[PDB]
């Protein structure tokens, strides 16, 4: 009775429409982020559903600017809109103040846009989760953000179908302030732990950034080196 | 103010001086008038400082966003066209500026843009109160067959001549060189001073 | 009880009204695209329906500009409105920047228009799929766009009733870098594989473009040679 | 339960409210158009029916401008509104460009207005089909347009209750390039075949136009010569 | 159930809410119009309800201007609002052009306002039919107009509860070009035939207009001669 | 089914919500008006209840201006708002033309405001009836006005719970052109006839106006003389 | 069926949502006002919960201005909004005319705001009753106002859970023109009569005002003398 | 039947949607506040998750300005929006008058924003409670605020799942004018007593302020001293 | 500025110079003032460069859209009418331009459009500060019987004469010929130089 309209609380105080948007997220490809010594990285699995696709296009990891990037899971078209919103919102801040001092504030603006779409009749929530990772004046940052506009800051985290396994793995295996290669190797292990019945991990997307540098996206051969 | 952009075979060189006046009153000796706005794109400013500084911030933000969206840098002509449209739109309440946009796409380019969004590409161009002095030097000494090293020397000569004759120009000369190989490079001021000494110049 | 309003997620995180719009797409004639050596082509099945109809005026293939064309499937009035949108939107980009550097941005604008019609009460999704194909500054491009505003870039792709048979055929048989005439022949074969019931392929519509050139529309005598 | 609202797709991707509006169109009086040598004509069945009624006004054939005419079937007040919209839209184009180069574009603006009424909550579709006929820069033209906003260009066609009979008759008997008088005769014959057995056709409305001239309405007597 | 909302078509293509509005019209007092030699008249029966009612007031026959009058049946407050609309709309034409050349365009503006209230959610139709009668640059005019915005031009017609009895009487007894006194006589007789079993006409309202003149409203002792 | 929204006609052409609004009016206290020789008067019953109430305010009879008064029955807050509207509307007309020539137009403005609340969704009708009485350039006037915006002009009339008793009494007892004293006496007698039997009349409100003067409200003393 | 929406009349002409809003008021704490010789007073009870509550921020009697105070009962947040409305509305009158001549007009503006919330869909009524008390040019005033926007002027009155008891007591015990001390005494007795078994009543709020003076709030120690 | 829309009163005068919003609040982590000598403090139970969460990043205690802090419980995204609102609303007041004289007005503006969201359809209530604590020109202040926009001022209070235990504990243990250190101790003591089954309080957040100073946030190290 | 458009039997010829000034100051020697705007349609610009350039972009966009939509080219008279409507709409905030629109539909056309949207067809026309000198040459030497080779020489002559007497005109002459057979064709600079040399001219 209580799960048809976003503006309706259940008697236990739940918003089931927001909870159902979360279910769209759980169906997306696994992605993870982790902090390492002076840096942050993102890795993304890619559901591949045809060799006819240009796979190096409509990518899961998206640059927001040179120092900040996002990865998403859930409805793709919704994810695109949120990444466009984050980009325009990053530039507005830059124009206003000359720079983006704290990435948390960008993340909150995206999360507030999402929150809005859980409070007004005649709109549905975005069926999307995001990890943001980058460097600001505080240092390397890793956030996530869900369909409700709930945000958390992490040392390591994941989204998508393999979330639970990847987080499990990382919770046992994760160490702070690893060097880059070792952080990347840990991340691939974690990703691989979520695969099931001898399922092979094709070359994921990987991007990293360290303090004083801009983002780099690992090309095809650098990633296979870890496979 | 004095600014200049020149094209060579595989390079753009852009330079300015730094004086900021209110009538005769030299308020600032080191304002900045030359900006990197993209990987292989530079912009010079002249005219009303507030208007020009807002345009610089916009162009930085928009070209970075365009690059992210398109996976390639905005072509230099497309930069000039963007500015042309933005400035003509507010024609009757204008940005009171003269801009040079220089860069490398498949070729080197320099565009001169006026306060009504008139935009013309040229082999070289100068803006500000000191520009007629610069056009004198360039008309007399510029060659398309110049090397980057001679091009750098020419613009220093041209802006130094303008500083001698234009009281609204002065201060240190900032120079940037843009190539496909090294990208946008602002030359170290010690290198500029050394060239100044060697050319036999003052201030 | 979850499939009646576009703004209502099902408990499994699905938007059934969007899914139902994609059923409308499956009823359109088949159209395909494929990238070939320095080029891209489009082919469209013409479901002929009476000698009383003007043949020349029915076009499934539509020029967006001289370097960009589209073919559509699904609700025809909807499709026509999307093509109008894409045409105005291309010209706006060309006015602003002087040219259209990357076709993916045009397709994304169209896809955003569609996505918006899946998020707000009081509106229905466009019951349309599009294939966009052309040359930009990156090279030859081929994209599809569905009722959700989901986009993918392809080497080869299809839409309409015979989508699955055509995609299947192309997964088996397509290779990159074919000369124009072999790519057309392969596309006609892919198209014929979808007909079934010993059905005769009537003269389809074909268009291609190669780097440095403008679109050409095959006249009907030229299409016959492949029949 | 998918047929109560225009913004609701059925599980097969249908819009039942739009199909119900078509049903209204099938109830009107039969009208037809045909292209002939250097021209196009329209004939309309006049279901007059009461001597107290003025047999002079609220005609089925309406001039849009001097070179373009339409005939409608379905909801009468809706039809009048669409005709008013068409006339104003023709003048807007003529003021903007000095002339109306291609009649298809006028028909598309009328059809886009219809289409919009099948996409937004709080409005019903127009319960109307139109045939447009005239001469533009391309030559004689003949279009139809339904409640969905779907258009087709024709050599001959019909609307109203006798549509199916009339079209059957024409698919068998229609010939391109008839002189005017034989086209009219064929059209009258076509229309007689649609009547329920042993029911006499009273004087229809007839209008025609030829390249280089303006429309003419056939007067009450000139029609009789064909009865 | 397809009969609860004005924007809902039934499977047969009907708008039941509009059909129900025309039931309200069947409950009003009978009125009629008829053209005669160089003129037109209107007659209205009034349901008088008590000697405490001031009878000179809230007339059934309302002048729209000096050359045009209307009489209404159905929802009385709805009808008053439409008569106000007609009056202001008549004046707008007269200001714009200097005169009202063709009464049909006035009626169409009224009917267009009514058609609107059958197409948009959140409104109901006007529960009203009108007869308009007057003289324009064409000659004497008689139109009616129903809740759907449907209009017809007539020689004689009626609205209200006695419509069916009045119209059948006129069908057999009406003749064109009667002198004024004979038209009125027939009109009175037509009205008397609609009354039930030994009922009596309580002096109706009568108004008439002839070419080159303004409207005249018959006074009590003038109507008295005809009873 | 048909009685839940004002925008919904029943199959018989009725607006049940408007009829239910009329039921609120029937629960109000009886008031009457009547014309006498060169004037008009109002009498209002009040079941005043508790001695803790200030009897000398929130009057049933409300001056609209010096020459026009109203009395209402039904929802009290609605009535207040309609009276506020009538006062402001009267003054708007006076400012525009310098005077109020015909009270009927003021009544129509109030009744049009009520009519509109029976035609647009999102709103309920006013649950109010009013009588208006006053003097204008035509003479003494008396009107009633109901929740539908239906108006009538009267020689005598009543509203409220005892309407019918009062009216049947006046049907037999009322005479035109009585002097003021005899009109009030008859009015007082008409009101007593509507009482429950054994039930007595505890000093009504009474107001009157004659040609050439402004309204007088009868003081508490002068009313008693009539009881 | 008829009690779910504010815009729906029941068949007996009732507005059930407004009646349910009046139930919210019955749950609030008891307050009363009464006129005395040259003055008026208000007394509010209230259940204090914890000893951890701050008294003094205790908020029952609210000054509207120096000459006018209110007490409310029902939903507390609704009541705060209406009290802010009243304060700002009193200042607007004071700025416009330089003073507030008649407190009744202030109460009407508030009551009009509450009436509107019983007439438009999309909004619920305020679940609040108010008593207003003060001095204007007429003299000491006492009014109540309920969720429907219904107002009465009183010599004595009460609102909240113990209303009926308090009104009954004052019905038997109230006398006009008491000195202030006797009024407060009677008020306290009336309030005490409304308590159950054994309660005794902790210190309530008391406020009074007399002609020529501004309001005084009796402080804790003054009130004690009456307990 | 009566618990599905915020604009619907139940027959007992309840707003069940608002009551259901409270239920979300109850699921949140316990927080408390208390006034001490010249001061006020807040303590918040954090509540865990993995070692992979950046600790000290999405604080439960939020500075509104240098003199005012808030803590929340319930929906976290809603809570963030209300804190952003409170921060902007404080700065608006500071710009207008130069300072924030009385914190109660800030709490009222926040509570009025929440109240609006219980009165207008198409909107859901904020599923949030807040405690505000700070110092103004009146002294140390402590308020709570619930989903209804109901506010109370306190000496001590709590919100979240452990509220009743914490409040019960404080209701016997709480002393008026304690020194900061002892106030903090009592607070932790009270907080511990709400944990069930020998559960271990990991480091909570603490903040305090005393007259003439700005807020201090205790370091993780400084809190331990109390654990 | 000097621009010219002439019609012949089955041809339109359009030409401009390239000088861009701010008062006496020659900023650009090689600005562009003649544009193809549709398959068989060209346009020249004069007046404020930013206004003109925006109008060139609009016409290229709109003429392309129209042709896509209509499957035929906009008639030249329709182009002129479109422009005339747009300029007149904003006549109190105007595009400060003089425009030539020339092309072939069923016949050759040249239209002249002013800043208030006044539009007139003529057999030839000229705009800009140099136009009076041009009208001198055309009045004396234009014939409707000229061949395309002759008309090309004629406009080179007109413009050369204008450049001698109008200091706001200068630089290389641009020329396009428009026909049904070849469409809009820009003449190569080497061919114009060769004709300037053959005709006995300078600048």
Image: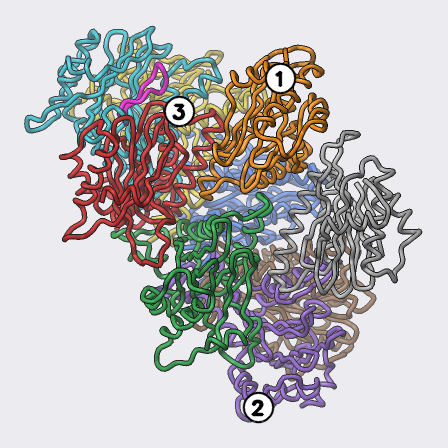
Chain colours: A red, B orange, C green, D purple, E brown, F blue, G yellow, H cyan
Q: Position of residue A9 (x, y in %)?
A: 28, 42
The residue singled out by tag 2 in the image is D199
Q: Are marks 1 and 3 on the same chain?
A: no
Q: Quadrant of residue E222?
A: bottom right
Q: Position of residue H9 (x, y in %)?
A: 32, 42
Q: Does residue B154 belong to the magenta stretch?
A: no
| The one of D63 and D156 positioned closer to us in this rendering | D156
Of all residues, the one furthest to the bottom in this rendering is D198
Element type at marker 1? helix
Q: Position of residue A177 (x, y in %)?
A: 22, 27
Q: Are marks 1 and 2 in contact (CB under 8 Å)?
A: no
Mark sitting on residue A101: 3
The residue singled out by tag 1 in the image is B199
Query: Disc 3 and disc 2: Cα gap in Å?
Result: 86 Å
Q: What type of secondary structure mainly makes up the magenta span?
A: strand
Element type at marker 3? loop
Q: Does residue H68 belong to the magenta stretch?
A: yes
Q: Residue at x 14, y 19 (%)?
A: H190
Q: Quadrant of residue A212?
A: top left
Query: Can residue A158 be seen here?
Result: yes
Q: Position of residue G86 (x, y in %)?
A: 46, 26
Q: Which residues are magenta?
A: H58-71
User: Which mark lies nearer to you, 1 or 2?
Assistant: 1
């Amino acid at each position: 009775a209580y799960d048809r309209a976003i503006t309706v609380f259940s008697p236990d105080g739940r918003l089931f429409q927001v909870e159902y948007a979360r279910e769209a997220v759980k169906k997306g490809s696994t992605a993870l982020g982790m902090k390492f010594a002076n840096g942050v990285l993102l890795i993304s699995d890619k559901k591949v559903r045809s060799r006819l696709i240009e796979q190096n296009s409509i990518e899961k990891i998206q640059l927001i600017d040179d120092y900040v990037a996002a990865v998403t899971s859930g409805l793709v078209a919704d994810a695109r809109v949120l990444v466009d919103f984050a980009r325009i919102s990053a530039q507005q801040e830059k124009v206003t103040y000359g720079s983006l001092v704290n990435i948390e504030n960008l993340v909150k603006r995206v999360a507030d846009q999402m929150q809005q779409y859980t409070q007004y009749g005649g709109v549905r929530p975005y069926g999307v989760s995001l990890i943001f990772a980058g460097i600001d004046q505080i240092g390397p940052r890793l956030f996530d953000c869900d369909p409700a506009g709930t945000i958390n800051e992490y040392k390591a985290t994941a989204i998508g179908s393999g979330k639970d396994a990847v987080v499990s793995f990382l919770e046992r295996e994760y160490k702070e302030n690893l060097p880059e290669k070792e952080a990347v190797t840990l991340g691939i292990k974690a990703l691989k732990s979520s695969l099931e019945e001898g399922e092979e991990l094709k070359a994921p997307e990987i991007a990293s950034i360290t303090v004083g540098n801009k983002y780099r996206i690992y090309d095809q051969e650098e990633v296979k080196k870890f496979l | 103010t004095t600014t200049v952009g020149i094209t060579l075979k595989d390079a753009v060189i852009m330079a300015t001086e730094r004086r900021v006046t209110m009538e005769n009153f030299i308020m600032h000796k080191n304002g900045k008038k030359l900006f990197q706005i993209d990987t292989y794109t530079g912009m010079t400013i002249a005219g009303l400082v507030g208007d020009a500084q807002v345009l610089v911030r916009y162009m930085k933000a928009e070209l970075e966003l365009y690059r992210l969206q398109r996976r390639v840098n905005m072509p230099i002509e497309a930069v000039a066209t963007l500015l042309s449209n933005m400035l003509n739109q507010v024609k009757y309440m204008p940005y009171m500026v003269q801009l040079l946009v220089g860069g490398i796409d498949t070729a080197p380019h320099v565009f001169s843009i006026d306060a009504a969004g008139g935009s013309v590409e040229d082999i070289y161009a100068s803006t500000g109160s000191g520009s007629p002095f610069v056009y004198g030097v360039l008309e007399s000494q510029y060659s398309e067959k110049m090397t980057v090293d001679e091009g750098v020397d020419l613009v220093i000569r041209a802006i130094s001549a303008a500083k001698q004759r234009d009281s609204a120009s002065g201060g240190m000369i900032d120079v940037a060189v843009i190539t496909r190989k090294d990208g946008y490079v602002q030359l170290p001021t010690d290198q500029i001073e050394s060239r100044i000494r060697k050319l036999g110049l003052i201030l």
